[PDB]
Amino acid sequence: MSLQRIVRVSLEHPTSAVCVAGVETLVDIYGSVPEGTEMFEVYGTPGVDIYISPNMERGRERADTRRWRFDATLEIIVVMNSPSNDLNDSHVQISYHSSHEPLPLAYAVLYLTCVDISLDCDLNCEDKRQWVWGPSGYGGILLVNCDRDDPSCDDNCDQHVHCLQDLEDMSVMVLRTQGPAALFDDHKLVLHTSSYDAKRAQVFHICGPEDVCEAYRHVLGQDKVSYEVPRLHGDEERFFVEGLSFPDAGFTGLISFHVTLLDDSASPIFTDTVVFRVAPWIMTPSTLPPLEVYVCRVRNNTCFVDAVAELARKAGCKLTICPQRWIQDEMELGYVQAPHKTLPVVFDSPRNGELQDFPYKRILGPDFGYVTREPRDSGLDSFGNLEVSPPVVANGKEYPLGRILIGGNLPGRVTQVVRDFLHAQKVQPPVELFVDWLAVGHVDEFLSFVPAPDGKGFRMLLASPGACFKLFQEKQKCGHGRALLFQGVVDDEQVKTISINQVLSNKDLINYNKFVQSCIDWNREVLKRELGLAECDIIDIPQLFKTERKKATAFFPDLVNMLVLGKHLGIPKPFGPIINGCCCLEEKVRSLLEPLGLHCTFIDDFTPYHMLHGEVHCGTNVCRKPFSFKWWNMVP
Amino acid sequence: MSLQRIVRVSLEHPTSAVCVAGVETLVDIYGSVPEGTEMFEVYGTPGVDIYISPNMERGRERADTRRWRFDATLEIIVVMNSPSNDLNDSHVQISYHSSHEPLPLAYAVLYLTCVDISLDCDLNCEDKRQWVWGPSGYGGILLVNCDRDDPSCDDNCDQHVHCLQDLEDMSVMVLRTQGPAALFDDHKLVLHTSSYDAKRAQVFHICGPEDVCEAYRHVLGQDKVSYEVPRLHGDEERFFVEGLSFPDAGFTGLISFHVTLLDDSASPIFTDTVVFRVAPWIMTPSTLPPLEVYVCRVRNNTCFVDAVAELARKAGCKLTICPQRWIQDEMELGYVQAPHKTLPVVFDSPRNGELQDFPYKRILGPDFGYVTREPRDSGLDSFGNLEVSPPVVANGKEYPLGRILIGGNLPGRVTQVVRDFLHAQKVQPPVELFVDWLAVGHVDEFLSFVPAPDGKGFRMLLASPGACFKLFQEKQKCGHGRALLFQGVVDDEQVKTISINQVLSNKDLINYNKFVQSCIDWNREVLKRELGLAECDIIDIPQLFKTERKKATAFFPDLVNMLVLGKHLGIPKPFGPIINGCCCLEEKVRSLLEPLGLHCTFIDDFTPYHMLHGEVHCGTNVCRKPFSFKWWNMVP
Ligand SMILES: [Ca+2]
Ligand SMILES: [Ca+2]
Ligand SMILES: [Ca+2]
Ligand SMILES: [Ca+2]
Ligand SMILES: [Ca+2]
Ligand SMILES: [Ca+2]
Ligand SMILES: [Ca+2]
Ligand SMILES: [Ca+2]
Ligand SMILES: [Ca+2]
Ligand SMILES: [Ca+2]
Ligand SMILES: [Cl-]
Ligand SMILES: [Cl-]
Ligand SMILES: [Cl-]
Ligand SMILES: [Cl-]
């Protein structure tokens, strides 16, 4: 199962073969044996393993212990597992014998120069030059290095390495080249890679160990496809490779680096390869523990920021604030994982105009990569539309990193470049949904995942006008139809206070909400099929819908469109019907959520938001702790 | 495992749902049930199947036979397996009951309009909307239709169908649309496909059955991505799809066609898809039975044509002749297979200048497709360099259609476009070899497969200078060293007659042939690894090599470079050393080949060929009978 070479010898003059450690070499001859050959012996220098074997069977046997009956169907294998100290310091001698004369008929001498050449980066073990998925898989992982680790950088753009810890983001690659030095006066050692892969990653050799930035010499890049390793350190050269791109429509995600020994007296005689896989971008669903909460602070945002602050302080989350409102629409905080340094990465939306500067200015710290996709020939659904489900099992397949959720229309959608990127990540197969019926059309407007210690660890919450129908009808059956919805609130336009009886007896509103629930039910069945969830995991949240056109906006603050930080969720305060001094919508929300251990804090956001068609989740972003499940053993 | 719909009803007014035959429909309600509901009954029109089932378990049970205790966790499924004869001719009625009053509390009525819509082409059986490989696989096959079946055509270029049997090359696609006619006054039926797939195939509707060419109306093409089926024939519309491209670097080979029912009062409510796979181009190795032999006839080709004729008449082969010599370098005759019409297809080389006109002029008959690949920014190895091995097993994988064999260099080759095409065929994974050492550098110069009823059904024959060393040395050991090689031949340049002693005692020639055999041995080991052959299947043919530069040409006529037609092979007549009135090279060739049942006829081609660096296989092409193994159950 190794490399096979055939080196033929002649009875007239000896040969001077060069072999690689561990590799087998078949030994045969040019021309015929002596005229009366009946037997033969073979001998080898210490450190030279010689085996005899028939060409039919594959059992090997030591060959330097007897006189073998001659047979053209036998073959001799020479292996040197250790490199030579000097040129041709070992040799093989084949003597041909006959029972007639006592002396050998002829000799065949082959001197050997053994060289130990090997290229290895990180053979993930827990094995050819192939990358395979699964728990029984192997292969090296290469990151994309999309951050700014050096204080001077304002990391993929430089052809130099001017940071002392940016190297932590790269992948090592060691080339051992043991053997006689004079051999390298006759033979070349060449590292190389295909030009396509050369445009996707860069390699740096080392010329002074671990201390000098200028010592990390760039050897492979955009135009540099090959390089001659001078063996500056001796018998081992160290390289650092950094990726330049993420898996995309045209890039499968694998890059090959080869080393080759050439005989320029040129003919190559050995080549070794190493295959890296570019680690993909992984999204974090709301079920994971949060790390940093992001929220804006605008000219009239007074208590929304205070509520987000005082409510994220319960889960121990950060509070980075932007001076310029939809901080969940501009960015999605995922990550890219490596066996050495897994770093979070922001994906910046092409929906620009308000926070278009925030990611490239105040989000890529030392360990914070940045990636973005802008189409050539516009986004209307963008990163409110981009969510991710928890790990699921459906259609027989298992999705241990969950699945991506994006919106669109069936007969015609989010831009094709973002779709191609998400589908090319290959680790969270997206599910395109029906969202075109909403005004802005974001997935998080009707769907939200919440952690709950029962059933599957989580509950999928869907907005349902039928749930609000039932709640308002049961309250009519109690007599509270005269309770008013928009009663307690700082008049933002003197919004007229409607009552339960007025809502239930408005034929147009009820029929439109029936249509809305039909849309959400189509999405519900698609979610149950593509995520493998049952009704035990699906909870309907009461929500009615307004409209000023053929598309749908929220009537009262959207209850699913909340901020989920582990055990604590910030929900927009539903300025619904007060029945006993407490909002009955809040009571229903509590009866549905608090039995799951969660704590519901409702935020007044009627004046800052919900009048510009947004809720707390639309104005609050969050990055989360990566999955415990590692992405390489995923078997797509 | 089918499509799931949820249609909600109201106790105030009935609903008018439209359903698809076979599809299940969950029935729920907007709002709550009557205030004192304890039980319920459900009833359905004949032909309406109603089942009750808990939302936890998946056992279904008929629901219209008892009064069920009310439970919100129960669900009712409605299925109509047969289309309706008139709008809303069937209905479901849900009555809500209490033990207090004897009459029903409330009713919920849902009228149903059932439509039977299905798109099917050829579900290969021996099952979703996916194409899977293997004996247990399914899916439709679409050809590329690269021939000229109509007498007027001079078939992928026309947007019309002006042939009566060109339709045999296309694939059928039937759309059944049973149901009430008035429904189609309210609903649209739309066939469609993605624009990428639209550029790869065309679809024609039928407006008059089986007789009129203008009736095969073009409905889907380069710009036409969607079409409205008018139901011109009633409850079933017939379409004919023809492919426009072969699998390539950017084309995986799958095209999807969808049908959709729209409600323009528009909202789609059902979509059905059909996935075709474009059949690839398959090569035929020399082991298969031949059909047609091609050979040129040039201004001084007198007996080579006669020998090819009189030697192909033994296997019952055709004899198409071109008036303009390398007919095996310009074209490769493969085929494309379909469950209805498998047609042979020529692949035209970009090595042009002598026979550049032959394929597009005198090779694409009625059933003979044409495909070609020309690079933007030149071929020096071309279709002498392109061969194919018999079915093999190696690296665990099984290659039942053999593997493709092309030449090149390791450290840098055949053009990248041809490589991408061959690799994208996906059915015969190519093996790139070392051929750069030869003058012209074609695979067939040193390698040829021959049928032999033993071992594996075939023998791989490799040119070997060591075999010629052994033969000439054993003849020296007999005393025939004074036998002359180029003795019997019509002087083409008064080529000097060399003898065995002169050859064996020429140090430069022997060393160069040793180097040549080392190259061929590298290729031999790569072939044994990538094809899984042993020495029992490998036969070495004696062949020496000349040179006028650093590259290698043949010394005497190349013995492997022969024409293999099943049981009969035409070999270039080796004008080698005559020892007993018979060429000893011919005697060795016979001793190696004739024990395999084959019959060896040696052709004098020294004056026509072998002086312009070519042999019989280089001047004779042949197409062969396709494999008995069908390509779809290949599991790549
Ligand atoms: Ca850097
Ligand atoms: Ca960095
Ligand atoms: Ca870093
Ligand atoms: Ca932006
Ligand atoms: Ca998001
Ligand atoms: Ca046609
Ligand atoms: Ca045709
Ligand atoms: Ca035809
Ligand atoms: Ca051509
Ligand atoms: Ca060929
Ligand atoms: Cl000898
Ligand atoms: Cl409900
Ligand atoms: Cl009621
Ligand atoms: Cl040999």
Image: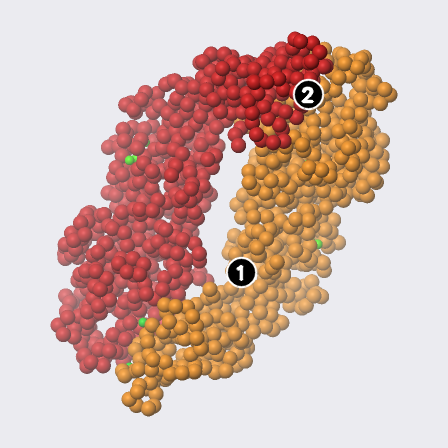
Chain colours: A orange, B red
* Residue pictured at 74% horizontal, 20% vertical: A471
* Residue pictured at 44% horizontal, 58% vertical: B395
Q: Position of residue B90 (x, y in %)?
A: 51, 13
Checking the image for residue A466, the label placed there is: 2
Tell me which amino acid carries mark 2.
Gly
Residue at the left extreme, as displayed? B581
Please state the chain letter of the residue tagged with numbered disc 2 in the rendered image: A
Q: Secondary structure at mark 2?
A: helix
Tag 2–tag 1 contact (CB < 8 Å) = no
Q: Quadrant of residue B593?
A: bottom left
Callout 2 crowding tier (Cα within 10 Å): few <14, some 14–19, many ≥20 = many
Closer to the camera in the image, A572 or B137? B137
Q: Earlier in the sequence, mark 2 or mark 1?
A: 1
- Asked if residue A445 lies left or right of residue B498, the reply is right
- Asked if residue A544 lies left or right of residue B533, the reply is right
* Ligand 7 shown in quarter: top left
- Asked if residue B360 lies left or right of residue B58, the reply is left
Q: Is residue B323 visible?
A: no
Closer to the camera in the image, A475 or A614? A475
* Residue pictured at 31% horizontal, 61% vertical: B455
Quick check: B329 above or below B279?
below
Between the residue at mark 2 and the residue at mark 1, the CA separation in whole angstroms equals: 57 Å
* Residue pictured at 37% horizontal, 18% vertical: B233
Closer to the camera in the image, A56 or B329? A56
Tell me which amino acid carries mark 1.
Asp
Checking the image for residue A127, the label placed there is: 1
Q: Nearer the viewer, mark 2 or mark 1?
A: 2
